[PDB]
Length: 290
Length: 291
Ligand SMILES: [Mn+2]
Ligand SMILES: [Mn+2]
Ligand SMILES: [Mn+2]
Ligand SMILES: [Mn+2]
Image (cartoon, rainbow over all chains, first blue to last red; front, top):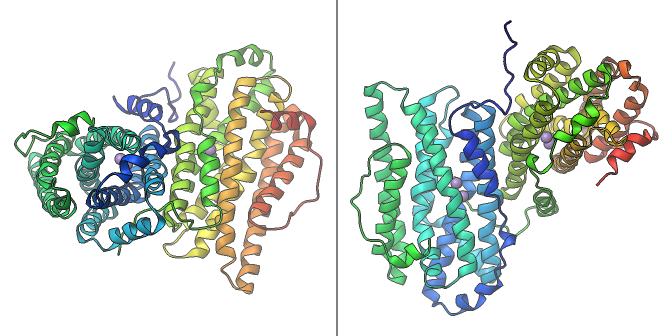
């Protein structure tokens, strides 16, 4: 009467959520080529030199983050997470990062900017100290993951949630700010698709992190919260300097800072933690950008 | 040390952007093909035909899982270049998110749960399937950081899987597909096979890049490695083939198909064909030429 036991298939749920994330991720599949970009040519031409500079640099910072999330972050987390369906979701998310998201920025650059300006902005990412610091910190945690060591994995998942749900947002602000004013709307459409993806990526990785956290003693949990909050504050302080560096020339630094604090709270919530920053009024233009 | 962003406005090689395009435009999902109508031809096959099909299918499934969990991600890890890593990530995604779900769907349609579990138990213990699966996995596990020789050897193993080892298995679904039997699952298999073909060609070009950076003595040594590996896999394929196909009388023709695909795998690695040219079973050809 006994049966022969199941061989890792697709009808069997590994958990309560992976299948629905799998379906959501694959149904959200897109390519930048679906969006024609020549319609932004005039609203781009009309921006001040300061505005164009900030815009290029903002997207370049995003490109760097997605490059490392696709090359390193998502594949390494996929390697250490158990279960073929969980791995399939993480592999799909990894593909989106570098094959779709990172590439879309080049589609935008190639439309709006001459080659020399494109070359210069990629040189600028290499030498920018805030962008290098944030990459160093995030990638360092990814590369510190030890096989069968759930704590090192948790730390990298916190880093990934902070990249998905917090760090992208100093960059996302500006395309959204323009979209909300009816400017650069084709580029803005691409960015909204990227943002829609990152929101579900941050939730999913957050749920995996909570799984590991929930296995710990109360004492260990207290240390993990310390790690998460210390890391958030360290990233936050660096992001403030990055934000000022980019946005002071367009007069928006204070507004962007409010936006990144808002999203920091969302990252904490994705990790099952209470909000850390007090609520503030976000620019309604950016809210219309959503 | 210095972290740089992917810049798709420039080429890092002669071929990666072209393969990127071909890969993403071939994107598909299991749900697109309705499978239930296969039961109308499945019920008319003999026990040996159903048995061979199940065993072949499980063989393909098991090998493709290794490629999704290890083969593609390990190569993506050691290859330098943002655009190459992106293409390789896309290929790994297809293995895990598309191909694996597609094989599962075919199984769930044709067999009850208990039968699926038993077939996988059998194929998991099978000597010829295990020999080739572990030979390939062994080479993936032997890649060393910053050692392009070990990477090349793994790429050769990967090309042999994509362009050669799958084909003793693909034969049967293509054979049915060419006869008007199991058309829905045959369409799925044809899409999978079309992905593996481009995977094999792409990884082959990455291997040739490494090969071309070597001295003449080192090249001769890498050629000997590739031919020796091919020979080991080929001799096991002949045994694998007789084990599965003698009961349905097809082994002679399957062997011709293996050699023909071995030659394609070698050409993907920039090497000369090893086997004399042979004609292929016209029913299988009719299956292959569909689309
Ligand atoms: Mn992304
Ligand atoms: Mn993401
Ligand atoms: Mn496959
Ligand atoms: Mn493949």
